[PDB]
Image (cartoon, grey):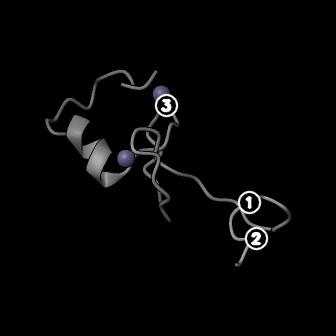
Amino acid sequence: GSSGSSGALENLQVEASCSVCLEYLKEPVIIECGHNFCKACITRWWEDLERDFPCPVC
Ligand SMILES: [Zn+2]
Ligand SMILES: [Zn+2]
């Protein structure tokens, strides 16, 4: 029996995470919009050279 693992009780550290899969990453791709996107995701949409395109999530 071991409790106390996850939670925001108290810790000096900030991190982000994808929006689609909601996975924890070290360096999330912050597109123009701002939302977080992982290579696995950001890629699914950024498949073509459609640089000019609105955020999918928004
Ligand atoms: Zn993702
Ligand atoms: Zn967005």
Where residue 28 appears, x then y in whole percent?
Answer: 46, 54
Per the image, the residue denoted by label 3 is 33
Q: CA distance from mark 1 to mark 3?
A: 28 Å
The CA distance from mark 2 to mark 1 is 8 Å
- For badge 2, the amino acid type reads Gly
Q: Percent x, y for residue 22?
A: 47, 46
Q: Nearer the viewer, mark 1 or mark 3?
A: 1
Estimate how packed mark 3 is, as few (under 14), some (14 to 19) or many (20 or more) residues with alpha carbons within 10 Å: few
- Of callouts 1 and 3, the N-terminal one: 1
What x and y, as percent, mark residue 24?
Answer: 50, 58
Proximity of marks 3 and 2: CB atoms separated by less than 8 Å: no
Marks 2/1 in contact by CB < 8 Å: the verdict is yes
Quadrant in the picture for the N terminus: bottom right
Q: Is residue 53 above or below residue 45?
A: above
The answer to whether 4 appears left or right of 9 in the picture is left
Label annotation for residue 7 = 1
Q: Is mark 3 within 8 Å of ligand 2?
A: yes
Q: Amino acid at mark 3?
A: Cys
Q: Nearer the viewer, residue 50 or 35?
A: 35
Above or below residue 41? Residue 27 is below
44 displayed left or right of 15: left
Residue depicted at 30% across the width and 44% down the height: 41
- The amino acid marked with disc number 1 is Gly
Query: Which residue shows up at 39% across the image and 44% down it?
Result: 21
Find residue 45 and report its image quarter.
Answer: top left
Please tell me whether mark 2 sits on a helix, a strand or a loop: loop
